[PDB]
Amino acid sequence: DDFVMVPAQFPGGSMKFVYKEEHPFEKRRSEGEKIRKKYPDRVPVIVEKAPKARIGDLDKKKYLVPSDLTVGQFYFLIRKRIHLRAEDALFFFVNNVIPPTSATMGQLYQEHHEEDFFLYIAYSDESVYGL
């Protein structure tokens, strides 16, 4: 009867990550399934610098994040890990879009997790992914 109202702001596609190139899909997927069962109130997240970003790199890519943590809290966390200056910008991208700062990480996971059961976030100094 009714139409599915496809959102005007629908995401882009998945993004390339060095992490996905360096860890075979079936190994990631098996790990993701297991970590979701072990910590069901947390979400597994891979965080990587976007292509062409001019910003410090993380020493750790893998984060197990409480599902109620907001995207804003996760920005605050990442800023501190790379000692961003007060005047430095930080943008996240999931499936090519900037996620809402007020979303929870659990909400982002539900909408954007990939087939390996991970959520992938790219970060940048720029507001356009890959620029």
Image: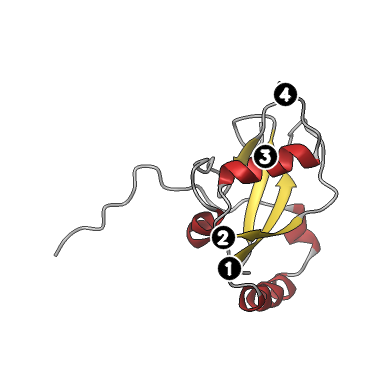
Element type at marker 4? loop
Q: Earlier in the sequence, mark 4 or mark 2?
A: 2
Residue at numbered disc 3: 76
Q: Residue at x 72, y 25 (%)?
A: 88
Q: Residue sitting at 57 percent across and 46 percent down?
A: 71
Name which of mark 1 and mark 4 comes first in the sequence. Answer: 1
Q: Residue furthest top?
A: 87
Badge 4 amino acid:
Ala
Dot 2 falls on a residue whose secondary structure is loop
In the picture of the structure, the residue carrying the numbered disc 4 is: 86
What secondary structure is marked by label 3? helix
Q: Percent x, y for residue 110?
A: 49, 62
Query: Which residue type carries mark 1?
Result: Asp
For this orientation, the residue located farthest to the right is: 59
Amino acid type shown at disc 2: Ser
* Depth check, front residue: 78 or 131: 78
* Labels 2 & 1 near each other (Cβ < 8 A): yes
Q: Which mark is residue 67?
A: 2
Distance from Cα at disc 1 to Cα at disc 3: 21 Å
Query: Answer yes or no: do the residues labelled 4 and 2 have beta carbons within 8 Å?
Result: no
Label 3, label 2: how far apart the Cα atoms are: 16 Å
Quadrant containing the C terminus is top right
123 sits to left or right of 109: right
Relative to 123, 104 lies left or right? left
Q: Residue at x 52, y 43 (%)?
A: 99
Where's residue 115, x and y in %? 58, 68
Q: Which residue is mark 1?
A: 41
Q: How many marks?
A: 4
Residue at (67%, 52%) from the top-left corner?
Answer: 16
- From the viewer's perspective, is residue 30 above or below residue 78? below
